[PDB]
Image 1: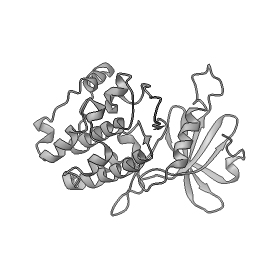
Image 2 (image 1 turned 60 degrees about the vertical axis):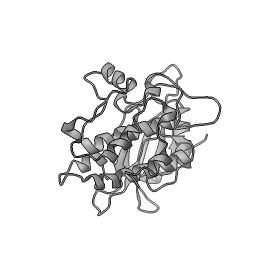
Image 3 (image 1 turned 45 degrees about the vertical axis):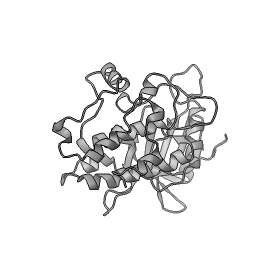
Image 4 (image 1 turned 180 degrees about the vertical axis):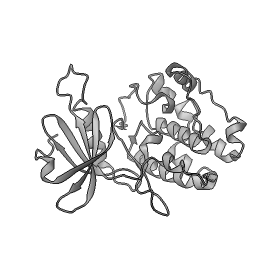
Length: 275
């Protein structure tokens, strides 16, 4: 697809560098016409099939396609897309609240009920995405942001749709990817993928959110993958002594190897722990 060919500097003022990925760098910018702040994500193009640097115009085309379709309070929103000879620039909503977990890193330690409030927002955004048959495939702590950390009730924002896919009927998807510690066995074992993968990740998130420890993180890359596939984890008393039976049941129904027997997003919203 053809994106805006005009120079981004004609419409925005470049600023500080918010973050930085492997094949992408994000900067803080301000639209000249409105004075409003946004985030500029520069994705370097591959433009050379044999090249292992940059992103293919198939992966870029896909992420923007998903983004352009998204429109929910708990998910990042796309403003504009530009491109030149070396980059594809995505002007995205500015999310400067930082990582949810780093915000919770502040004492006055979260009550189980207060923890549910934040998870609820995560479920809300996932609910919205799955309803559109969209699997994020990269749900983990660092992609769970806050719009503003200086308000009574901080709003969580789900970002980074670099791995997101549109689950279409017929023709399955199996590719291997993501971060070992937060991926589902179907991803590790190169098996057919669907929306059930995000639900697994959510269970990993809640597990960490409530205990502060990871359920499958091992001493090495191999050990972690083995813990995931074998779905071996425990609720050691040292971390789950103050966790209700409902909170554990909720996680158990998400950390299940068989994708078809794993709770769906709609099932999680009606779970007695979520109410």
